Amino acid sequence: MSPGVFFDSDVLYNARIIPYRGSWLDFEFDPKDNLFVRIDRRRKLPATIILRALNYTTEQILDLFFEKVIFEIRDNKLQMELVPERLRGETASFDIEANGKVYVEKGRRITARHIRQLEKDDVKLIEVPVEYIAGKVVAKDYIDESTGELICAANMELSLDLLAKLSQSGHKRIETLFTNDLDHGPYISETLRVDPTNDRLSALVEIYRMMRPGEPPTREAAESLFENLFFSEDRYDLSAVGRMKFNRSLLREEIEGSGILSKDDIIDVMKKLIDIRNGKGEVD
Image (cartoon, rainbow, N blue to C red; front, top):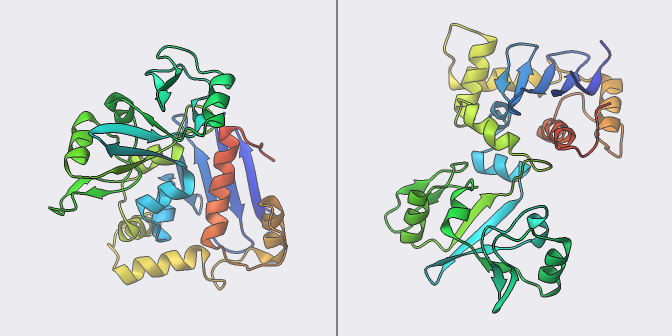
């Protein structure tokens, strides 16, 4: 097999990095839109494991793959920092209003004109009901900053209880994920849920168990094995030709580069694969 990177499908989309020397790296969607990785053509692992192994926290993972919807708690009411574009294609579930003007009545389909009216008047903050926020997925951990105790963790689905707790604790901003059911799908958020690993070490241990079943690894052994998979040229090389092909596929300006992979190489392949699923761009 010639070295390079490949984006294909079966519709279940996939990506594959074939090196000149070393382990293959595969990514693929399942029918539920969760994302999985294979190392050396071995069994599928929820794909976020490789990002954890590369030292990304859950919060950082969510920031790589999602825009944010910011809510504000104030006057014991709830507000949302509004990007009007995000309302496109929806029906209003509450009166969309600002500065004493109702722009969209509850139950009206939100039109291109409504969005333009909001944009023309620079409306960037609107009141929302608690039920609207309860749908959402929180983007970062929050503690009660007086007691120090955790209220919620990153990627948790919000609820009436958690919203009550967040409000009670004195928090005035809540960051959530922007997702939809079309071009901004929640794949990575859902993938974090099926991923049994929770941090870099547990990710490294899981990868080690998969490669070398039957002896639990030391921290040092797990770290070493992972570094040698894709990040040490004595064990992994994309050959110059491989790096050339890789870089052209991912739209790098230069065809020169390293035989080993970078975290950016891996992230960029995952991003492209996700783009394809979201419908921006196509397979090879």
